[PDB]
Length: 231
Image 1 (spheres, rainbow, N blue to C red):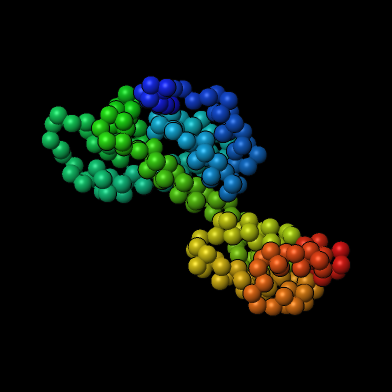
Image 2 (cartoon, helix red, strand yellow):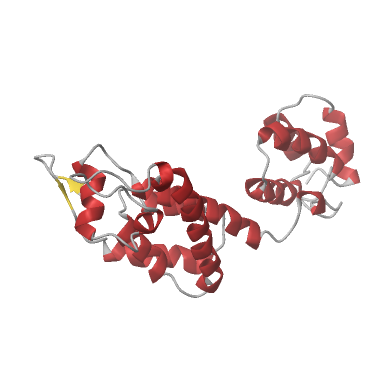
C-alpha cells in the first residue's frame, strides 16, 4: 500500500500476493481462532481501506458469516457517520471531502482520494478506524465461534489441569469483561471449576499463589496431566 520511500514520499503499492494467500491460509486452518484477531491487524499494517477491504473480500469459505461482519462494518460506519461525517455534514468548498462513513469503507472513494485525505491534509487514518471497526467485528466473531461459556468450563478428575487452564484461558481470551471482572471470576473458577483430586492440591495452594506457582505446584503433583496423581 502507501509506503514512505527512502525520500519519505508515500507511494501506493499492491499487497504482497504471498501475504494475501497467507491471510486466507491462516484463516483456512484457524478461520475463527482468536489469535487471528491480532494477526489480521498485523497483516493489516499500513493497509488502505480499499486494498484492505479487498483483503476481507478475498476471504471466502465461512465468509458467509463474515457477511455479518460486513453488516457490522456497515453499522460502525452508520454510527461513525453520526460521529464524524455528521460533525458538519455539508462543509465549505476548496477542501477534500471529509471521509463519510461510505467513504471510510472506500465504497465511495477513489484510491487516489483515499490516499489524498489520508496523507495530503493532516494524517487521516481511515484504515485505523475502519480496522478498529473490523477488530470489534472480529471480537464478535470469536464470540460467534465461542463453543462454551466460562461457566461451562469445568475440569474432570481424569482431565488435565493443562487442558483446563488452556481451555480456560482459551475461553478467557474470548471473555468479554476485562481482568477487572475476568481476574475475579478466574481466581474463583480456577479452583471451583477444577476437578476434586487436583482441587485437593489447589486447595493446598490456598489464597494468593500466582498462576505460575499454581502451575508449578500442579506440575509437581501431575495436576496438568490428570490430577494430583504424581504424573
